[PDB]
Amino acid sequence: GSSGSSGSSKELLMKLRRKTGYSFVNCKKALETCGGDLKQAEIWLHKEAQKEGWSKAASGPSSG
């Protein structure tokens, strides 16, 4: 349990990588936009996809 330059989210990035499945660079964005929140991070990526259209499959358009 040690670290160097305090100010980075890797442990969460690696986890969110397998959770959602999106590339590392991607998850990183959702993690920064949300603030290290697997939940608020998993929903983001999915949402962005629905709008942008990264993958064919339907992400899941929700209201409010």
Image (cartoon, rainbow, N blue to C red):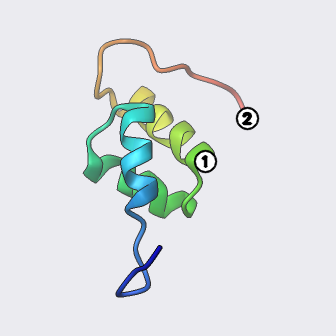
Identified by mark 1, the residue type is Gln
Q: Quadrant of residue 64?
A: top right
Disc 2: which residue: 64
Up the image or down, 45 lies above or below 53; here it is below
Q: Which mark is residue 53?
A: none
- Viewer-nearest residue: 18 or 35: 18
Residue at point 38%, 56% (across, down): 29
Residue at point 42%, 66% (across, down): 9
Identify the residue at the far bottom of this view.
5
Q: Are marks 1 and 2 in contact (CB under 8 Å)?
A: no
Identified by mark 2, the residue type is Gly
Residue at point 47%, 20% (across, down): 59
- Viewer-nearest residue: 7 or 4: 4
Locate residue 4, reporting x and y percent.
Answer: 35, 86
**Residue 10 appears left or right of 60:** left
Up the image or down, 41 lies above or below 19; here it is below
Locate residue 41, reporting x and y percent.
Answer: 53, 47
Mark 1 vs mark 2: give the one in front: 1
Disc 1: which residue: 40
Q: Quadrant of residue 17?
A: top left
How far, Cα to Cα, is label 1 from label 2?
14 Å
Identify the residue at the far front of this view.
1
Q: Earlier in the sequence, mark 1 or mark 2?
A: 1
- Viewer-nearest residue: 62 or 1: 1
Label 1 environment density (alpha carbons within 10 Å; few <14, some 14–19, many ≥20): some
